[PDB]
Amino acid sequence: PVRKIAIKILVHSLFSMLIMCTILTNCVFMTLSNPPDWTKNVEYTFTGIYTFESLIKILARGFCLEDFTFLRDPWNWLDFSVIVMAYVTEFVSLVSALRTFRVLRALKTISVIPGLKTIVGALIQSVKKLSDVMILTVFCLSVFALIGLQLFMGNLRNKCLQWPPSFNWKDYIGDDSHFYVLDGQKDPLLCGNGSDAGQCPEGYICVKAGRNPNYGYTSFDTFSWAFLSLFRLMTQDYWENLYQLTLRAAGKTYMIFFVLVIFLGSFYLVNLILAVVAMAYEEQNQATLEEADCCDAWLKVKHLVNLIVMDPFVDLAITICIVLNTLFMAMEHYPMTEQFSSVLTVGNLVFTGIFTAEMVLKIIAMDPYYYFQEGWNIFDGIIVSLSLMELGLSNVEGLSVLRSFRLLRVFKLAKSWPTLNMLIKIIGNSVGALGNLTLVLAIIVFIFAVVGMQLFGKSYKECVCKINDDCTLPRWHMNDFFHSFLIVFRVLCGEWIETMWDCMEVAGQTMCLIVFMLVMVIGNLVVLNLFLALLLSSFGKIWWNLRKTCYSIVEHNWFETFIVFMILLSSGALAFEDIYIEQRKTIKTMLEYADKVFTYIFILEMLLKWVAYGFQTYFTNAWCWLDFLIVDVSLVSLVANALGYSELGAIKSLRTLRALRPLRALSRFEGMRVVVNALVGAIPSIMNVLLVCLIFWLIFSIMGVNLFAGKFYHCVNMTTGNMFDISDVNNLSDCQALGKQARWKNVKVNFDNVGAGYLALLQVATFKGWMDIMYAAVDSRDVKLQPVYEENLYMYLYFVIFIIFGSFFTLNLFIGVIIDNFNQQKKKFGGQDIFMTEEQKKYYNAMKKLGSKKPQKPIPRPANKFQGMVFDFVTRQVFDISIMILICLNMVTMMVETDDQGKYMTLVLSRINLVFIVLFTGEFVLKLVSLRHYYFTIGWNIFDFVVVILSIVGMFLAEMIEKYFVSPTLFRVIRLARIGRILRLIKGAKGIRTLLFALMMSLPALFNIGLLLFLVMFIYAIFGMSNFAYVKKEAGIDDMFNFETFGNSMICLFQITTSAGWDGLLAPILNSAPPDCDPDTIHPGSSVKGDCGNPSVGIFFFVSYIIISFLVVVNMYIAVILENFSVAT
Amino acid sequence: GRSMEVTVPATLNVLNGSDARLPCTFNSCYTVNHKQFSLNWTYQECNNCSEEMFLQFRMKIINLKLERFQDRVEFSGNPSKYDVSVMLRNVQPEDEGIYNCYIMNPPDRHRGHGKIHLQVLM
Amino acid sequence: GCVEVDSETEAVYGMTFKILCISCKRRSETNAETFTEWTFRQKGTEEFVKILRYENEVLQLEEDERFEGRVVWNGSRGTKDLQDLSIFITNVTYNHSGDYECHVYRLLFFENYEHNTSVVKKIHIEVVDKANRDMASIVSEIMMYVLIVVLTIWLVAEMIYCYKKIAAATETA
Ligand SMILES: *[C@@H]1O[C@H](CO)[C@@H](O[C@@H]2O[C@H](CO)[C@@H](O[C@@H]3O[C@H](CO)[C@@H](O)[C@H](O)[C@@H]3O)[C@H](O)[C@H]2NC(C)=O)[C@H](O)[C@H]1NC(C)=O
Ligand SMILES: O=C(Nc1ccc(S(=O)(=O)Nc2nccs2)cc1)C(c1ccccc1)c1ccccc1
Ligand SMILES: *[C@@H]1O[C@H](CO)[C@@H](O[C@@H]2O[C@H](CO)[C@@H](O)[C@H](O)[C@H]2NC(C)=O)[C@H](O)[C@H]1NC(C)=O
Ligand SMILES: *[C@@H]1O[C@H](CO)[C@@H](O)[C@H](O)[C@H]1NC(C)=O
Ligand SMILES: *[C@@H]1O[C@H](CO)[C@@H](O)[C@H](O)[C@H]1NC(C)=O
Ligand SMILES: *[C@@H]1O[C@H](CO)[C@@H](O)[C@H](O)[C@H]1NC(C)=O
Ligand SMILES: *[C@@H]1O[C@H](CO)[C@@H](O)[C@H](O)[C@H]1NC(C)=O
Ligand SMILES: *[C@@H]1O[C@H](CO)[C@@H](O)[C@H](O)[C@H]1NC(C)=O
């Protein structure tokens, strides 16, 4: 016929390649920010070609006057959509809806190559298995959201308000100039009336009046806003700020709430999402894998060169020269004196020369073009050629940074190193076998990128001064394609809310909500799938006589418990050494003498341990050796202050080692003992992987030193703390000629050398700190030149690349090797369940026996007179489904609650939930009449009973508080029985029950690991109290959250525990010199001096806490995943 | 941005004798405030003749009704939703010329404009 | 930051002393200009007569003989924002032993809103010829010794009890 002609064209591979290339070039064309006139014609061409393919498909599966052919293929639906609304778009008056037409062409990128279809489908089945976890996640988010809503109902609205000299209260609340705008924040400061809350300055009072602490955004005074804020808490995006605002409004006492959600909403639900995605991917892998003359001279010199000593002290010498080359790369300082830069450049020339020499020696013993077959030789040739090109040019502008590719020589160590070879294998799998999936990621990111622009770009250009002070575009916009990619990449990283606020203030609420939620769901699902994909591809008369007695003393339970109590009291003795210690003068001396008592007890128990266990056995024990060291430092302190060297710079600095006193509790407790045993047993492989990670971050940090060698130095106007304009000041010369108002300030985190390079890369990879790092690196123009706003705008790519490699691949290898090590440890050598002791093991086994229990219908009929009637007409489906419907309706009534709802609305809701509580009491009593004898065989019945009792008691308590001595801060807390009234949902909600049971199963191991973590926070909080209770009031450290007291230190360390905002807490400590801090500022009521902590101990403190918390949280994660696997498989 | 977008047409002709509604509205982003807005209408008489004044409303309801051209203008705008316009009292053979509608919105920095030839057809 | 500490009540005759009065700001970041007055009544008098005044740089004194050439300033040194108010009294005598009132008047600056706050700190001192140790310190030291000796007795008693047990038990073989 004639359709047969339109078949060969359809299946011909050149047609598919044409479609691929036209989609790719159209995609490159959507990148354009402001398309010139002529491009329009090309755009027409594109849609014409698209019509082409549709024609080819529409004359291929329908014959003899047939209408629809490509409508059983879902992607053909998208093709039909784009071809139709392209010509609908061709009628411009038929409109500001281009944003819904161009994006349809944007989504067409998915089907560039066959194979992405299967990957998208596989992602679809992966998200299909997310039903139970997503429903549990939304339920928990809603529950904690109502908790936060009825607790902080409008407290986040609290602000400082002046006290008037005397319309009245109408244009006083709504002035926004009568509020305390904290300097350099452009957002009114929060306060509160209760204690342990934000303090309104002298001359202000805290009033619940104004907008919420943003442009009017994710606060707690609405259920929708509460749900958004707790989705933010569940993803932990910038939750330091929500933490700070909530605790500044409602008081520090409420922080326990966060400890719940952070441990329950974020820590647990993320783990469950990861675990179920992992099970889906493992099932996918299991299914897929179970389914399937002159030649005489040349040869005579080859005789020697191939015989030139290969293994002894040459190839090993070549490797050690590679290591020395990396070393010479390391000493790249920013502040450089001559005769040092000369040394480095002559060493670099020597090394590129020796590499060229060895290459020409290896291409005359394996032939010039037979040599390019091992693969490693190809890589060596490419890298040596790049080095030779760099030395030859030495004059290219903007591209001398290609120099850094010489660091690729480090990867030659992969020939010997097995673990870095595993890293290279993971990279190859990312680009190779799983590259399709990786491609999807990029494509999806690209899609959202362009989509974002088409939906928001123009808006961000016109609505700009709505969000700014200079009305120029913010540093994170979508006006051009690159920034739209950057925002999507940042959303993938996890920092979404800060830009989402800007979007929602520029381009309305619903559009940006939908866009950013779609990105955060789809893109993170893709990223997690890729991460797990690479993860799963990893694989005599007195002596003895007294000795026995003292052994019986030291082994007895009485003495051990007394010693444990002394440990707790001695550790607590440090907590009272506040900023407020001198004001007491009674606890001060009391704890001073308690120090002597505790040291005496400690020395005596050490002596009994000495005389009982014996010196050899007491020094073969790590715990006893550590205890002896701590007793030694305590005894040295006692000798010092008895003799009188107390106020000596070295001895007083040694006094801060008292913070290690709680460390001896590790041995006495079972939980810390077993958890530290597991950690320090797994520490060798962790150390090997850490060696690999510091090697690869050394590569990236030396690259960063080359890219940003001390170019961060920017002038600042010392009356406002702001950068200069390029016009007024350009470089170092005029910055030194700008009187004294110019500082030539640094960034305090930079790339001056591999040390600061490691610090900055740690901040970037943890994603909490990259703000000023990226901003200044992009600002970086050149040495001694003042930075310019987004001048070197493409340096973002570097960080992007780093985050892909040094934070997504390195952490991937780290987690994979930890998975392998723990697998080996639990299965082969050791107990099957680490992090739990023997008694905890018995608890776990008894709970396992308890969980798989069901009743063998031991409920006979009641006695007489219609009790059996209700008994038998209550058990049926009707009653249970009805009570769940009433629970859900009560939940919906709960969500209606809002700030500033009229007294009538409160009365209506009170009547409605009176109706609900009565209908639940009559229900409880119906089941009672059904089962008057016992009714307590199953814990769900006793849960219903206790929750109904709690609701009634809370109801009466609310009435009492509302017609007696009244306090709203107690009413809000006591109103929490309704939360259990809706938690009653768990009884019949299958799936949720199993996952919460997994929580209950993992609770012992999580408790042990979290007890070790709490001890770690205790030690670090006391050390910070000793050190950083005196730092300046910079960004992260302020009056409310700082290291002054123990409560403030513990809340700061809880903020840090999830790596949140530790950049802000490290910023003030990094101050070292008079320009930033001041070494002699006498504090009122303190004999101490100086308001800046020691930088070295500051970095050590924060980086050590980050690493220890990361290891502890990884142990928690592994425990949860183990529980999920055990319950499921 | 480059300018301020105005939904102004090219040229519109209104029959004589009827009441004249002279429209010029701009679709901006920023939430409107009825206290600080700026609005000045211009017109080009000769090739490069300097304007004197055409309309007013630069701080509040301010009217001109100048006898230089005609007796006209009635406030028929409502800036509440990006829509401010006026009227003209009597379309006559003395209603011809290029009558611009320059604008200025305070919270942004763009002086937008729209040019239409006020004439008569039939 | 800043901490409010109650000054020591017991001074010493003939020695020196430092009367403390710390009025910490509610917010540490607020720029302010602070000055103060110190008004003392002696034991046996019922009034509060001005004796010391502190302003931006130099303090002024009333011409009372009880403090002429005798009191110096140990507040915050030249910061225009005092936040620390202590009088260092040299060669303490009997004629200053009674009640001080510490009126700290702080003009808090703000964006455009000037505040004029006043806070009173009533401190009590009693000059004494002999600097006896405070009750808290003596009780603390005595209880320290009691705890040490009691625990030593406890451990020696436990050792002797276990010695009796092992003598009764191991003597069999
Ligand atoms: C924290 O405690 C302060 C101290 O009482 C509370 O200040 C009180 O604020 C309310 C309004 O927020 C004042 O009510 C009056 O309302 C009329 C209009 O009905 C208005 O004309 C008055 O000027 C005044 O605003 C009340 O007088 C005021 N109390 C005092 C002693 O100043 C504040 O509301 C509390 N905030 C929270 C969140 O607990
Ligand atoms: O209505 C009332 N009090 C009330 C309190 C809180 C809630 S509540 O919305 O916050 N839900 C809750 N669940 C657990 C705790 S509170 C609802 C109602 C009183 C009432 C007033 C007028 C007519 C009828 C009753 C009342 C007084 C004595 C005994 C009961 C009720
Ligand atoms: C630093 O910038 C100043 C800018 O003033 C340079 O001084 C000269 O400035 C004038 C006008 O400002 C320019 O026309 C000259 O071109 C500048 N000189 C040069 C050599 O370019 C100053 O030279 C700069 N110095 C450094 C070290 O960058
Ligand atoms: C410092 O800031 C002030 C702000 O008013 C400005 O006037 C001054 O010019 C700046 N100083 C410089 C850049 O010389
Ligand atoms: C103390 O004051 C009394 C007032 O009567 C005076 O007589 C006496 O000399 C004073 N002594 C000293 C040491 O100032
Ligand atoms: C108190 O004042 C004396 C005398 O002026 C001075 O020597 C001493 O250093 C001061 N002490 C403090 C803490 O200001
Ligand atoms: C203090 O005064 C007494 C007598 O009033 C005198 O004996 C003593 O030396 C004085 N001490 C000082 C330090 O002035
Ligand atoms: C207000 O400030 C002035 C400034 O000198 C001061 O004299 C006055 O005592 C202050 N007001 C009060 C009530 O103290």
Image (spheres, helix red, strand yellow):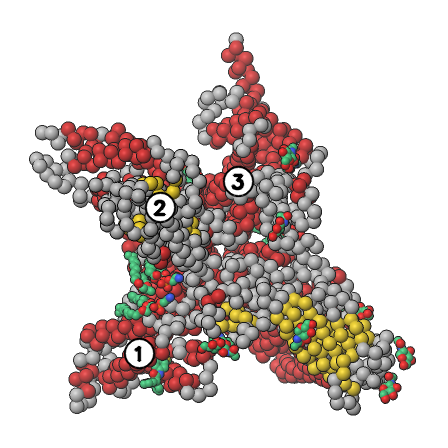
Residue A101: horizontal and vertical position, in percent?
28, 44
Please tell me if label 2 and label 3 are on a single chain.
no
Residue A687: horizontal and vertical position, in percent?
55, 50
- Give the chain letter at badge 2: B
Residue A85: horizontal and vertical position, in percent?
24, 43
Task: Name the residue type under label 2.
Answer: Phe
Residue positioned most to the front:
B67
Spatial CA distance of label 3 from label 1 is: 60 Å
Q: Secondary structure at mark 3?
A: loop
Of residues A624 and A864, which is closer to you in this image? A864
Quick check: can you spot residue A710? no
The mark found on residue A557 in the picture is none
Q: Which residue is mark 1?
A: A908
Residue sitting at 46 percent across and 81 percent down? A967
Q: Quadrant of residue A309?
A: top right
Residue sitting at 52 percent across and 8 percent down? A293
Label 1 CB sits under 8 Å from any ligand 2 atom? no
Q: Secondary structure at mark 1?
A: helix
Q: Secondary structure at mark 2?
A: loop
Task: Name the residue type under label 3.
Answer: Glu
Q: Which residue is mark 3?
A: A791
Residue sitting at 54 percent across and 76 percent down? A166
Quarter of the figure with the C terminus of chain B: top left
Spatial CA distance of label 2 from label 3 is: 54 Å
Q: Quadrant of residue A628?
A: bottom right
The mark found on residue B69 in the picture is 2
